[PDB]
Amino acid sequence: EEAPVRVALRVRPLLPKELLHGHQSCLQVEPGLGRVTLGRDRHFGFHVVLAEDAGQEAVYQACVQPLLEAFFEGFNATVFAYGQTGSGKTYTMGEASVASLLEDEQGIVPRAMAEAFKLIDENDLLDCLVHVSYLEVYKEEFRDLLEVGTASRDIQLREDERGNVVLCGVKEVDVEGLDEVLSLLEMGNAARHTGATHLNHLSSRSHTVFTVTLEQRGPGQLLVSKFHFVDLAGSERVLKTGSTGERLKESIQINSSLLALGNVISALGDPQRRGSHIPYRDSKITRILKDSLGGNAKTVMIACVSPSSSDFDETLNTLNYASRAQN
Amino acid sequence: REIVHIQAGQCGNQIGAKFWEVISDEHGIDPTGSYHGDSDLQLERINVYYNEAAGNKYVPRAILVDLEPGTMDSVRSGPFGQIFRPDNFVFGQSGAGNNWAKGHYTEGAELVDSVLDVVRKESESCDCLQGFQLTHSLGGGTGSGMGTLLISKIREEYPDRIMNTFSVVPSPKVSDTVVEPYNATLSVHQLVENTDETYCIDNEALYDICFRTLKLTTPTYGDLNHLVSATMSGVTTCLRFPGQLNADLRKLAVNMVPFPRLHFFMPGFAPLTSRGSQQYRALTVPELTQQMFDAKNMMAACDPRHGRYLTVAAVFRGRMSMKEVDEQMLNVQNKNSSYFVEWIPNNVKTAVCDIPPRGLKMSATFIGNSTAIQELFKRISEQFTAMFRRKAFLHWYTGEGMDEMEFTEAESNMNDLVSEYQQYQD
Amino acid sequence: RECISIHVGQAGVQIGNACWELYCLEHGIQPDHVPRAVFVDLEPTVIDEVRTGTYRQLFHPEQLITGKEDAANNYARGHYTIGKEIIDLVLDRIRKLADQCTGLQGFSVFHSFGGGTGSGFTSLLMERLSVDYGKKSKLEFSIYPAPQVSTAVVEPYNSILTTHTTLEHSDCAFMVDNEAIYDICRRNLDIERPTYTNLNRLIGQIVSSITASLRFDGALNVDLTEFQTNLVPYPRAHFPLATYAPVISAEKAYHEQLSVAEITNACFEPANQMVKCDPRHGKYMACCLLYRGDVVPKDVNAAIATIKTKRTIQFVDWCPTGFKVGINYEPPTVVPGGDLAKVQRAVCMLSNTTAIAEAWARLDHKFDLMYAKRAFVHWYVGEGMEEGEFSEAREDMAALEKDYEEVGVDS
Ligand SMILES: CC(=O)O[C@H]1C(=O)[C@@]2(C)[C@H]([C@H](OC(=O)c3ccccc3)[C@]3(O)C[C@H](OC(=O)[C@H](O)[C@@H](NC(=O)c4ccccc4)c4ccccc4)C(C)=C1C3(C)C)[C@]1(OC(C)=O)CO[C@@H]1C[C@@H]2O
Ligand SMILES: Nc1nc2c(ncn2[C@@H]2O[C@H](COP(=O)(O)OP(=O)(O)OP(=O)(O)O)[C@@H](O)[C@H]2O)c(=O)[nH]1
Ligand SMILES: Nc1nc2c(ncn2[C@@H]2O[C@H](COP(=O)(O)OP(=O)(O)O)[C@@H](O)[C@H]2O)c(=O)[nH]1
Ligand SMILES: Nc1ncnc2c1ncn2[C@@H]1O[C@H](COP(=O)(O)OP(=O)(O)O)[C@@H](O)[C@H]1O
Ligand SMILES: [Mg+2]
Ligand SMILES: [Mg+2]
């Protein structure tokens, strides 16, 4: 019941304002060969490579359709949105995307709930209940996005006797339709568009958490599956050094969380280190990915890479990060 | 630079009591009276642990917290029971029950905000704050629950300073409270995310030193608190006197821990002699260099030889030569060099003060971090999960707001805290 | 102009304490002119040493600088925020001293690497001096890390990040280490209590052999600016090694049929030169000397001859001759509490060798071992640093050792 890591690579097409300053390209996507020509010499292989002509349904059929069977067979499932701020993480997840009006332009989030009810009524023999939970992580704290406010000092983590990550103080809604899902994610995004209803001070620098969960019970074999919608922060790194006195703790948050996550994935890099101690306990977003990373779970890595040469070294850092973690 | 002191628990109360009764004698402070140092050298840095009010009184800037009025009433009637401003006594009349969660959920929350009021009064009372001294025990929600509840509100309040934790971890073979060891797991679950420096103290090593190595037969608790007071007095104000090469708390913080998982510490006081007989002409750093690094003279319950070393933090004081400091330290870097793990080349940190103590000519103080604390918290984990299972006298905690998942997450946090030292022993 | 100097670091402050005591004795400076320098440290206690008893009465106290914040011994914290609050007052006081002097000569800098406090403050201080007074003389002495006699746990990382600021902000640089000075105090001083209070006397002795009674009243000067383009081969700011030879006792060492040539030849003996850069394979590119006491220059152009005809202490192939001879009339001076020799002639030396890269390898491999496991990185992230500065410091040392590889022994 333990499976290795699956990797998806998708290039976005070029936005106008990143071309209006007189920029050019730096990539050459090889979909059959499975790598890209970054500049001249950098040829970095992956599992699933898609060019800048990809929709959300192409990535959906490529990766999420094998994830949906495993989620309807009692296995944990997790997809996460990594990439540069502006490289299309919010587009890749597409939690009930609206403004991108066309039907191929909303993401995986309406599509999975559209394909759930085709098999929910067919799996009426086993007890099948689906509940959702939408959260935000910022400043090494939490935010209940199904709530107008709850103190992050009052919400903490747990862990069960079986050995999996347990939450508390989180609103759960047993969903029965796509209307409730997209309504609560309209409200979720309507109450945290810039970041938990507050002046955008890089609200995309935060983390947001969403989770779909299905139980299984008939002689009563309790194997509960989860279909996680993880939405991470930006892949970029801010030097920040003197900004407002000593208040560069936001850089301390993202740099500590991604150096911790980098030591985790680089502990999976060397196979000598994958028997070692995996430091989940350095960050909250690493502890929420504890059982998600391997075990009985299912993992598809997506890093939204940038097409243009204006993002050359940053997309290089992204490709280095995915080549160390992309597995 | 300014530091305040916390007293939680009856054991922490006794520790703080004997600590003030030592450190005021080092500066030459009569109890009601004033400075009486025959040199001016005892006076030059007294802004650290005192505050001037009238030229005679020098109030110890400290905190007095208990869930029972009788223990601190015994303190205020004792030897130095007039040196405290009595408003610093903060206490409820409620029960001092041995539940961690009694001191952390309900019967501590009745008394949190008064302590917050006192520490906000005393932090910005005066000049730039430096650190915090937490003395408590794990054997009571006074020290375990209310202690971690205090410092967990402190580190969200003050993300800047240094949190010195003086904990009393229950020894495994001498476990004088049979209903104890849940509180250890609940305490260490919320120590490892808030403080930075924890000098864990174990009573059985104190009994070992004073009862085997010292020939003093009666193990009166005043001697134990006297030794712990000497141990902590060889740390801070020793480095806040004139010194040849002096450090602070923050230097030892950057020196000792590898990671920000803050990697608990083992204290040690070097010169231990039988009362009058042990005059032996063996007085140098060298004898003390050997005296620090044995299986005894180590306040851990675990054996510190059994495992690697991370960082030797040695504190020296007295007129002495640095060449025969570093030469002895090179001998320690060469003899035990197998379990003195190699990839960190310098494992030694040197702290040199000028002054001796009041009576002794030369003394030293050892602070240590080894992998051997794995084989102390593994033993505490074993004593936890052993009688976690049968539950029959576990339902005291359930109706106090404690839930089932909290114990298991505490178990996993303490257990992979053990597992990282299982890694770095090799 | 007496090279108005700066001092920082407890090592630097105490070494300036003993050095300044030697200064105020060697000219007959009564405790009733002006101290011509500044003392800055991020801890008030080490400065309050001198601000308590001796020399407090001497100094006008309104001109020394302290920091009431933490000690902060790590390059990141010492360079950044916690040292930011002090630098401007220091700059205004040293520009006051630049205004009161007239035709000054330069800057002698005394600090250390052993701890970040006297390193990053030092770093941006030298940077701001290169911005302000870059068309001057910048001499720097720092106490070099020990290969195995080391004291700080965090000993490499400070020096590793400090190898950038010593490159493009000074030209001549001195890096003398504790270890062979302990060897001197055991061997040639003949005592068995080496305390820092004597090592400070030794460095004060070598700097008093450089500068003081040479410049102040007297007439036989040898220039600092005639060092900084007479000691580097090529204007990459290389790293010469200075050594004070007659370190023998005035108590037991009554070899009183002593001449110039003994300590002159002892300037080139390997186990006496206060660093582990013996000429096992390091060669000599420039060996400018300074003599003080009595000089028959036949001793000069006979010791130079008998060194030239050894063919064991082989010079640089491309550098034909590299000598410059400092001759001063006045003897050294012995502090009454000190231990030095009171001899009517004395020789300090200074020379740049090839094998500084050996000590750089001793520091470099030591850095890379703890860098490999990402050891102490969270403190430096906590005061705003990055991996790329570590990479640039590593390749900086790599470029320095390649430069010492080609331009040295190789022809
Ligand atoms: C003249 C002299 O030094 O006699 C000592 C003495 O001989 C010895 C036996 C003392 C004696 O202490 C003990 O035997 C002891 C008992 C219980 C717990 C720990 C120690 C002494 O009690 C200790 C005490 O030594 C001191 O005064 C230190 O400064 C000590 N201060 C206090 O103990 C103190 C006394 C009254 C009120 C408050 C404090 C100290 C040293 C370092 C750090 C903190 C405190 C005294 C005079 C003596 C005796 C009485 C025999 C020793 O201990 C200390 C801490 O000094 C044990 O070996 C050391 C040094 C000596 O060998
Ligand atoms: N030769 C010599 N070396 C010294 C002396 N004092 C200290 N050192 C060494 O030089 C290094 C620098 O001293 P530090 O005290 O750390 O100076 P710093 O880096 O500014 O840090 P601070 O402690 O805050 O002053 C130390 O690590 C010692 O090993 C001294 O008096 N003489
Ligand atoms: N060494 C030492 N340990 C003590 C002393 N008093 C108590 N202890 C230990 O501290 C543990 C907890 O004491 P504490 O929590 O402070 O008492 P409480 O506040 O009434 O709950 C007990 O298990 C004792 O073993 C003392 O005077 N000396
Ligand atoms: N591959 C893509 N195809 C079409 N549109 C895209 C793509 N990637 C990004 N976009 C558009 O860019 C806009 C902003 O991208 P966004 O998802 O906010 O970036 P990020 O979330 O990574 O900061 C979105 O509205 C989306 O419509
Ligand atoms: Mg976006
Ligand atoms: Mg110093």
Image (cartoon, grey):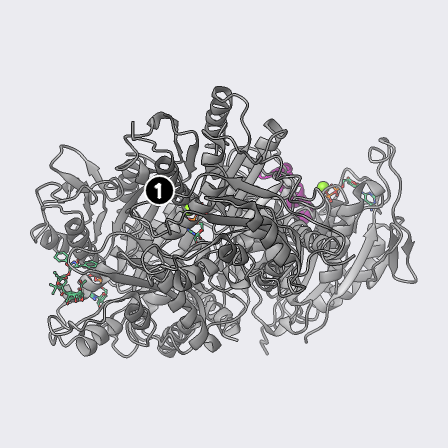
Indicate whether residue A184 is drawn in magenta. yes
For disc 1, does the CB lie below 8 Å from ligand 2? Answer: yes
The region drawn magenta spans: A180-197
Residue A141 visible to the viewer: no
- Residue B426 in the image: x percent, y percent? 53, 76
Residue A318 visible to the viewer: yes
Q: Is residue C59 left or right of residue A278?
A: left
- Residue A109 in the image: x percent, y percent? 73, 51
Q: Nearer the viewer, residue C46 or A38?
A: C46
Q: Quadrant of ligand 3?
A: bottom left
Q: Is residue B23 left or right of residue C358?
A: left
**Mark 1 surroundings within 10 Å by alpha-carbon count, few (fewer than 14), some (14 through 19), many (20 or more):** many
Residue at screen point 59% across, 79% down: A219
- Residue C391 in the image: x percent, y percent? 67, 52
Residue beneath label 1, please?
A: C46
- Quadrant containing the N terminus of chain A is bottom right
**Amino acid type of the residue tagged 1 in the rendering:** Val
